[PDB]
Length: 192
Image (cartoon, rainbow, N blue to C red; front, side, top):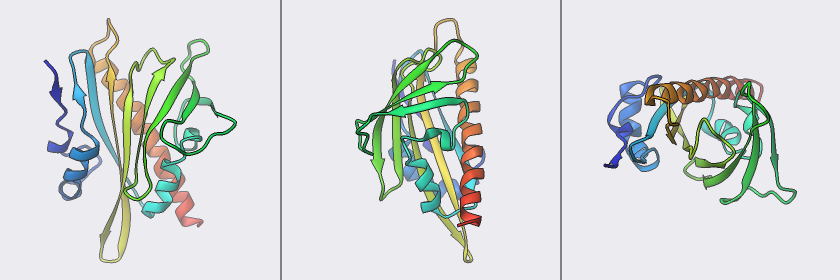
C-alpha cells in the first residue's frame, strides 16, 4: 500500500555524513512524504559558501523562482501579491513543447526556521501533483561558515513512464537549480 519516505535514514549525495547527522531531525520533520504506488520522491542537497540569511533571501522569493531556477520563461503573480501561504504564481516553463504554464501554490513559509514549500496544482503534465519543500541550514567549523540547502519533492509518475525516468528528470532539474542557487548566492555573499 502506501508508505513513508526514508530520506532521513540515508545520506543524500552532496552531503557529508557529519552534515547528515546534524540534519536528520529536520529531514524527518520537513522532508517526509506519504508515498503511494505510482509516485516517487527524492531529497537533494547542495552546500553553499554563503551565510544562511543570504541564501534564504533568494529561496523565500516565491514570486521570483527564476532567480535560481532554470527553464523558466516567465513567472507572474497577482496584482496584489503578498508573500503569504496560499498565494499562487503562474510559471511558464521551457520544455520544447507548446505553451505550458504551471500554477503553483505557496504551502509553507517559515522565516524563522528557513522552510518553504510549494505544490503544482495545475498545468504541468510531466510533474503532476508535484509537491516540494526547501530548507536552509547553517554550519560552522573554526569560524568558517557555510550553508546546506535541502530540497525534496514527491510527484506522480505518468502512465507509460517508469519511476526511474520521472525521478531522473526531476532530480536533474532540482540538482541544476541548486547549482544555480549556489552560484547566485555565493556571488551575493562575496559582493555583499
